[PDB]
View 1 (tube, protein in one colour):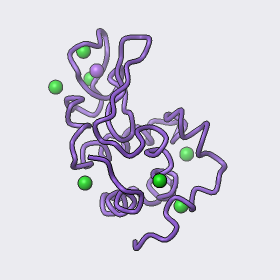
View 2 (tube, helix red, strand yellow; view 1 turned 45 degrees about the vertical axis):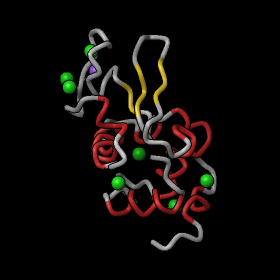
View 3 (cartoon, helix red, strand yellow; view 1 turned 120 degrees about the vertical axis):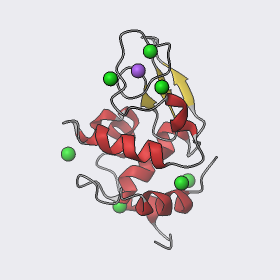
View 4 (cartoon, helix red, strand yellow; view 1 turned 90 degrees about the vertical axis):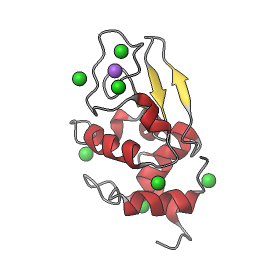
Length: 129
Ligand SMILES: [Cl-]
Ligand SMILES: [Cl-]
Ligand SMILES: [Cl-]
Ligand SMILES: [Cl-]
Ligand SMILES: [Cl-]
Ligand SMILES: [Cl-]
Ligand SMILES: [Cl-]
Ligand code: NA
């Protein structure tokens, strides 16, 4: 599913991400824009053989099982395919674990490089929330 901006903001708010671990909703929408262009089916293969999945590009080295990342963990206890659903629940529940892990949203390279320190409220401007 390719979300609209406001559609995704609303879905993320309903799933309890607004101000989760102190990160305002616009941070999450900005991260999703630059990780996946709001496409739940986004996948990208990494040099180390791991793969990033879904709207928040969650990596199989640590967070999900894809059966092809040797020596990896599955800390969200989910198949990586769950992260590609039109239903963002699994992605959101796993992102909550990741952002609690100690480096906050710096775990997302696109957030650190493209969202951090910017006017992220712009990403939810105009939306009925
Ligand atoms: Cl947009
Ligand atoms: Cl915001
Ligand atoms: Cl594996
Ligand atoms: Cl594990
Ligand atoms: Cl599995
Ligand atoms: Cl959803
Ligand atoms: Cl933090
Ligand atoms: Na894994």
